[PDB]
Structures are given as C-alpha cells and as structure tokens.
C-alpha cells in the first residue's frame, strides 16, 4: 500500500535504491528504426529512442519515423503518446502524428529554452495573425485563443488538413515551471494542472491518445503519465490499496525507455497519487484547495 511504503522508504532513506532497482528491472527492447542512419536528424538525443514495437509510425510514404511511443495501458484503459520536443525539421511530422492519431490534446511539460539551450522547437504559433503552414505534411496551424495562468497556459489551436480542408481543434496545456530533472513546485500545483487536462475532455477514449512531451519525452513526461494512470486505476476500482505504483511504472517502461528520470520524480509521483486519491475517493473540495495553493492567477 502506497502511503505506508512511502513512509518506510522515506524513513530508511532509500529512494535512490528503490529507483535504481526500477532502472535495473526495466525492459530493454530494440530501437533499430530510430538508429537507422537516415533517422539521425530526427532524434534530439542519441540515447533516447522509441522501441520499435511501440513507435508511432507516420503515414508517409517516404520515411515513417518519428521519435514517439504509444504507451498503451491495458488495465487502466488509457493510452498516451510520449515524444521528444520536436526539432526544427520534425515539427511537420509532429502535427502529422497528432492528425493521423486523432489526438485532441498535447501536454507540453518543458520550455523552449531551458538552462540556456534550445530544448524544443517553437512548433506552435504564438500569435493569432501568424499561422504556421507545414508544407511537407500539408497542414496549417492557427492559434485561436490562449488562457495564461501564473505557471501554465492553455491554448486553443486549429489544425487543418490542407489536402481535405478538414479542421480540428487541438488543446495545448503548457506547464512552464517544471524544471528539467526536477519536480513540480507542489503536489497541488501538479494536480491542479492534471485535472485541467482531464477537464478538457482530451483524455476521453473517444479521442486518439493525448500527446505528452517534455524535451526528451521521458522524465517529466513519465512523471505525468504515471500519476495519471495510477489515479485512473484507483478510480476504476474505487480502491487506493489496489494500486502498485512501481509496477505501473515498470509496465509503462515496456513502451518507452527511461520514464521518470530521478528518484525525486518517483518520490514526487507517490506524493501526487497519495494526494490525488483524496479527490478520487469522494472529497471534491480538495480540487478548489489545489487551485488556491497553486496560485494560478
Ligand atoms: C533533457 N533530458 N535529457 C534526458 C536524457 C536521458 C538519458 C540520455 C539522454 C537524455 C532526459 C531529459 N529530459 S526530460 O525527459 O525532458 O525531463
Ligand atoms: Cl516556452
Ligand atoms: Cl535559460
Ligand atoms: Cl530545437
Ligand atoms: Cl529547467
Ligand atoms: Cl532511466
Ligand atoms: Mg496579438
């Protein structure tokens, strides 16, 4: 049971050891496509690749490769697409994947510039009047509106298939204050953001899998999906005791390497799930309290 286990690990000071055992137990599957010489410029990080079995295939034609994985959580019945922050030459492929996979929401957990370096291309338009046209993949993208909060922004985008003239609405949830190899400021601030995402309808099974990315699409991304999946699992069952967090994380790591990148992100995951279980188990009031504690205005 997660809270008792939490207290025990904390007491004995063993988060590093718990987290290293997850790393040693994690699946190791090939990534031969990601490593094809022709794909080298499609990859942000040498050592972060999608497994071949789980990779998202683009429906071109010339090169179906994108660094994106489908994390398909069978028992939870939710999927997520985890991807690296798009590169200057992969922004058209990224929107192509969103279109082909029928995603309604993209959760971005990083900034474009972190620590002085460019960790993600500016893949969405920051002004209504300056849309983006991705000529390679025949798509256009328009900022429709944005809602700017203290630590996150929600943007409404319109994606258009230029070939068919079909248009879809895409919600962009942008967490701007989650440091790389770091944790959110509090469980409240993380949960307030997660439930904004849930509220939008973007995780509905009527839509394709939500796209989640940070820079490498593994540490901040894995932290997000983990907490969400664990909360979903206990909601299904109405039973917090039935959720084994480390097991869920190991199941996720069958689909993408390196999910959750520090011991403290693991520890933060347990805090978020333990705190969010209050909501799942019937205390609707805590939602209002997370909003306050998050200082979103
Ligand atoms: C910036 N970065 N770099 C990694 C990583 C891990 C192993 C090898 C190379 C990069 C993960 C991450 N970031 S995160 O996934 O964006 O939080
Ligand atoms: Cl940014
Ligand atoms: Cl900086
Ligand atoms: Cl970039
Ligand atoms: Cl950072
Ligand atoms: Cl790892
Ligand atoms: Mg303006």
Image (spheres, helix red, strand yellow):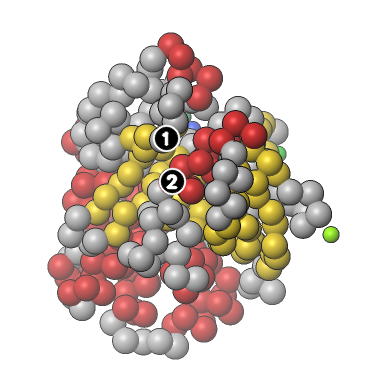
User: How many labels sit on residues?
Assistant: 2
Res 174 quadrant in image: bottom right
31 on left or right of 146: left
Image marks 2 and 1: residues in contact by CB distance under 8 Å: yes
Residue 179 point in image, percent of width and height? 57, 47
Q: Identify the secondary structure beneath mark 2.
A: helix
Label of residue 100 in the image: 2
**In this view, 175 is above or below 285:** above
Q: From where the camera sits, is residue 5 visible?
A: no
Q: Identify the secondary structure beneath mark 1.
A: loop
Residue 106 point in image, percent of width and height? 51, 54
Q: Quadrant of the N terminus?
A: bottom left
**In this view, 114 is above or below 73:** above
User: At 56% from the left edge and 36% from the top edge, which residue is drawn?
Assistant: 137
Binning the other alpha carbons within 10 Å of mark 1 as few (below 14), some (14 to 19) or many (20 upward) gives: some
Among the two numbered marks 2 and 1 on one chain, the one whose residue lies closer to the N terminus: 1
User: At 60% from the left edge and 31% from the top edge, which residue is drawn?
Assistant: 136
234 on left or right of 193: left
Q: Quadrant of the C terminus?
A: bottom right
Binning the other alpha carbons within 10 Å of mark 2 as few (below 14), some (14 to 19) or many (20 upward) gives: few
Please tell me which residue lies in front, 160 or 93.
Answer: 160
Please tell me which residue lies in front, 137 or 194.
Answer: 137
Label of residue 58 in the image: 1
């Amino acid at each position: 049971e997660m809270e008792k286990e939490f207290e025990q690990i904390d007491k004995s000071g063993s988060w590093a050891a718990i987290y290293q055992d997850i790393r040693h137990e994690a699946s190791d599957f090939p990534c031969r496509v990601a490593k094809l010489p022709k794909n080298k410029n499609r990859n942000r990080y040498r050592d972060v690749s999608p497994f071949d079995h789980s990779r998202i295939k683009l429906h071109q034609e010339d090169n179906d490769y994108i660094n994106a994985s489908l994390i398909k959580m069978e028992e939870a019945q939710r999927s997520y697409i985890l991807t690296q922050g798009p590169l200057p030459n992969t922004c058209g492929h990224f929107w192509e994947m969103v279109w082909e996979q029928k995603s309604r929401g993209v959760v971005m957990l990083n900034r474009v510039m972190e620590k002085g370096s460019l960790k993600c291309a500016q893949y969405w338009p920051q002004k209504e009047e300056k849309e983006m046209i991705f000529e390679d993949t025949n798509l256009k993208l328009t900022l429709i509106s944005e809602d700017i909060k203290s630590y996150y922004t929600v943007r409404q985008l319109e994606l258009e298939n230029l070939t068919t003239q079909e248009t879809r609405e895409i919600l962009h949830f942008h967490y701007t204050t989650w440091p790389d190899f770091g944790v959110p400021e509090s469980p409240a601030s993380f949960l307030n953001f997660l439930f904004k995402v849930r509220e939008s309808g973007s995780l509905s099974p009527e839509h394709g899998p939500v796209v989640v990315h940070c820079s490498a699409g593994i540490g901040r991304s894995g932290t997000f999906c983990l907490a969400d999946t664990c909360l979903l699992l206990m909601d299904k069952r109405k039973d917090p005791s039935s959720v084994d967090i480390k097991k869920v994380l190991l199941e996720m790591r069958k689909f993408r390497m390196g999910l959750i990148q520090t011991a403290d992100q693991l520890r933060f995951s347990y805090l978020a799930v333990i705190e969010g279980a209050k909501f799942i188990m019937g205390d609707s009031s805590v939602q209002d309290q997370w909003k306050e504690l998050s200082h979103e205005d």
